[PDB]
Length: 159
Ligand SMILES: NC(=O)C1=CN([C@@H]2O[C@H](COP(=O)(O)OP(=O)(O)OC[C@H]3O[C@@H](n4cnc5c(N)ncnc54)[C@H](OP(=O)(O)O)[C@@H]3O)[C@@H](O)[C@H]2O)C=CC1
Ligand SMILES: Nc1nc(=O)c2c([nH]1)NCC(CNc1ccc(C(=O)N[C@@H](CCC(=O)O)C(=O)O)cc1)=N2
Ligand SMILES: [Co+2]
Ligand SMILES: [Co+2]
Image (cartoon, rainbow, N blue to C red):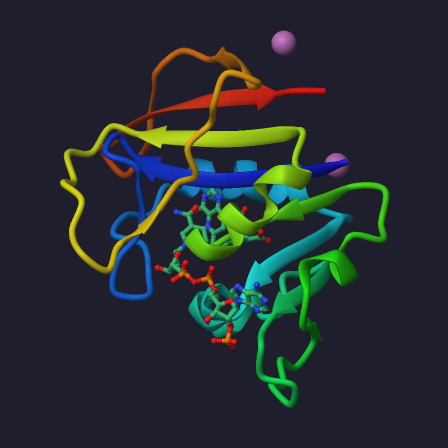
C-alpha cells in the first residue's frame, strides 16, 4: 500500500518559498495519525522543510529521496530512487510536488486536506498532483480550524 498525503489550497498550491503558507493544527494531527508507525517518503526539499524539532518525524521510518549520493539526513535513510523506499506494508509519500508526481503511479490512496484559502498559483509554487478518472473520491464536510481557515478532508482511492 502506497498512499499520498497532502494539504492544498483550493488552487492546488501545496508549497511556496520552500515552505507552506498556512498551518492547521488539526491537519497536522490528522497527518500524524495517518502516518504514525509507517514508512514516510519525502523529497530532499521537504526534509529540509521539516521543523528541526520533528526531524526525523517520530515513530516512523523516515526516507528521503535525493540525487546527491552523499546527502546526509540525520535520522533518515537517504535513497536515490523511489523504488528503494517501498519495502514496508504501508508507505506514505509526504511530498513535495516533485515526489508526489513521481509516486502517483504507485499509489492507491490519497488523503487530501483542502484548505479554504484563496491562493492563486505563482511560478515556483509546488502543486498537488492531478487525480484522473481512475480515482474514486470520498469527501467529508467542511470543518473550522482554530487557525481561522475552513478545511475538509478527501479520501481518494483506487485499486
Ligand atoms: N502542503 C503539503 O501538504 C506539503 C507541502 N510541501 C511543500 O512542497 C515544497 C517542496 O516540494 P518540491 O519543491 O516539489 O521538492 P520535493 O520535496 O519534491 O524534493 C525535491 C527533491 O527531491 C529529490 N528528487 C526529486 N525527484 C527525484 C528522483 N527522480 N530521483 C531522486 N531524487 C529525486 C531531489 O533532491 P536533491 O536536490 O537533493 O537531489 C529534488 O531536489 C516545499 O514548499 C514544502 O513545504 C511538502 C510536503 C507536503
Ligand atoms: N495533510 C498534510 N498537511 C500538512 O501540513 C502536511 C502534509 N500533509 N504532508 C507533509 C507536510 C510537510 N510538513 C510537515 C511539517 C510538520 C509536521 C509535524 O510537525 N508533524 C507532527 C505533528 C504532530 C501533531 O501536530 O499532532 C507529527 O508528529 O507528525 C509534519 C509535516 N505537511
Ligand atoms: Co496507520
Ligand atoms: Co470508496
